[PDB]
Image (tube, coloured by chain):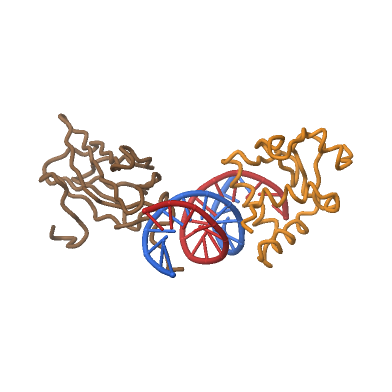
Chain colours: A orange, B brown, C blue, D red
Amino acid sequence: GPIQLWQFLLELLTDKSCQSFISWTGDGWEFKLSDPDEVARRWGKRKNKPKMNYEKLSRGLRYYYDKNIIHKTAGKRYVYRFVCDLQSLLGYTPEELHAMLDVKP
Amino acid sequence: LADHPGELVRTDSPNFLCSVLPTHWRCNKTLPIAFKVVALGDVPDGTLVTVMAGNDENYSAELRNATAAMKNQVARFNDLRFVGRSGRGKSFTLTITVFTNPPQVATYHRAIKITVDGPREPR
DNA sequence: GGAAGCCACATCCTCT
DNA sequence: CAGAGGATGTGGCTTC
């Protein structure tokens, strides 16, 4: 269906299988694409865009800065932070979510 | 209405002419032809000129670089753009204000429709 | 049904 | 290379 980038990432971040290439940092809604190429590959696959890569996926994310959906964590490679209201969306404080996922940090 | 035959349209004012604008353009996209306001009478170099767009949908539409200085009878608007949309099937009316003393205002009715996509290839 | 709108990217590019 | 944004066409959907 009409899946959006941020929603797609949020799905990966709530699937413990994907923790090797994308995960929460442990700090609120901040997350990291530890393996950008893989995330991009998948995003590409979900949207049917074989040529998709991190360089283009990151452009997607950058459009969010303005829309206050996601912001960049300055200084941290492949690190962003959901700035929208996720608690409302998934009814869980980050601490509870980090617990369900056994997020290390 | 001579030296640049189809490059100028008349405004509701007999002392001013402005470039012809696209009938329909994409918002925030650069115009294909630099918008210019031409003064027939004597308008001192340096005179400011602003343009405001709007219709029954936006009494005031958000623009960009909507200011220009009159140099030798012509106000050469550098990269002027329309940000606010004008509504489905409706166009903006430009209000040109030439800051002389007293100021003068010329109008360009139903001058341009602005949409999020602008002119687009059929699907 | 279908043109005309809006929103989200997908791509490419230029700088820092 | 990573990362900011600018420019411009396309896919999905909604409005009239």
Name the side, left or right, on which A30 lies relative to A67.
right
Name the side, left or right, on which B38 lies relative to A25.
left
Outermost top residue: B102
Residue A77 picture location, percent across and down: 75, 45
Q: Is residue D5 above or below residue A3?
A: above
Q: How many marks?
A: 0
Name the one closer to the observer, B97 or B61: B61
Residue B79 picture location, percent across and down: 37, 49
The quadrant in which the N terminus of chain A is found is bottom right
Q: Is residue B93 above or below residue A84?
A: below
The quadrant in which the C terminus of chain A is found is top right
Name the one closer to the observer, B100 or A79: A79
Name the one closer to the observer, A16 or A38: A16
Name the one closer to the observer, B34 or A11: A11
Residue A83 picture location, percent across and down: 66, 36
Name the side, left or right, on which A54 lies relative to B44.
right
Residue positioned 25% across, 45% down in the render: B93
Residue positioned 28% across, 43% down in the render: B55
Residue B68 picture location, percent across and down: 29, 41
Residue positioned 73% across, 40% down in the render: A90
